[PDB]
Length: 140
DNA sequence: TGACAGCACTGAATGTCAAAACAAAACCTTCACTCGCAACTATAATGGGAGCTGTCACGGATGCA
DNA sequence: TGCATCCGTGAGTCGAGGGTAATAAGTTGCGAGTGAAGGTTTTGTTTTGACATTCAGTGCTGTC
Image 1 (cartoon, chains in turn brown, cyan, red):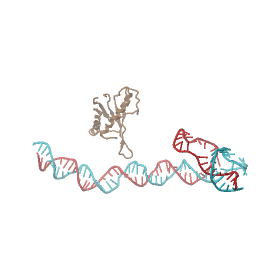
Image 2: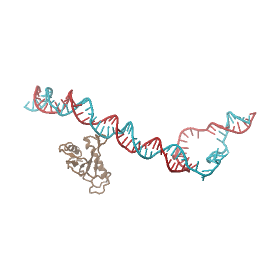
Image 3: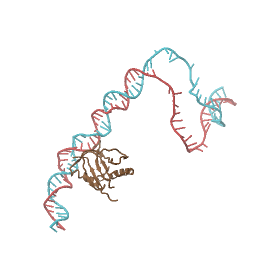
Image 4: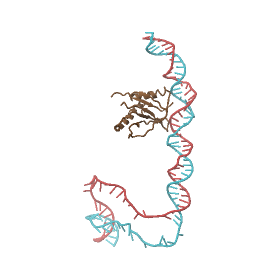
């Protein structure tokens, strides 16, 4: 529960300690990352909500993945490949320039569901200019 | 020369009179049932101690006799 | 004038481990009190006339 500028300042740790707990027992490095944001309103007065953020490990070439959590089936329907070049501090303004601008300036209405993030940890000191997709479930 | 400072006034955009509705549970009816009282039953029956408690110890006491 | 009897008294501060267990009749009648929660009532968050300003708006007005 944080600010507009803290829409990715808080979100940096929710992928990292989730990754480095599993990397202590991972013989590989899974190179496709998945993050899921959720908007769920209330029932008492319809002015409030809460957000449960789920980063996940990919069902990839390593079959045995003993990770705490849930087997999450990704939502189907229309999506958008918002590929990017920039560091996780640059997805801070990239999430804000897709959601402050690219939903008005491309005039699109994102649909109900989990906003799929597609980071790339395959290029994980210099500041890393990573590549990432923001696969929004869209209703065009 | 062009900035550079300040004025003229629209008006959309505020700050007030009203309701408009929605869940809030809050207090409140309800209405069927679960959960409780009370009475009777007719061959014959008739007297506890329920286990208990066993010698400390000098001392003062009151009332019987 | 003794002789029995009947009450009422008895270290200090600690300590441990911890409350235990008989037996007995039912059907039938039938009012009273959780209770299903049925459903209202309130006690608060939202629409619309206003018009009085206000700054926003755009341009001019005047100026270094």
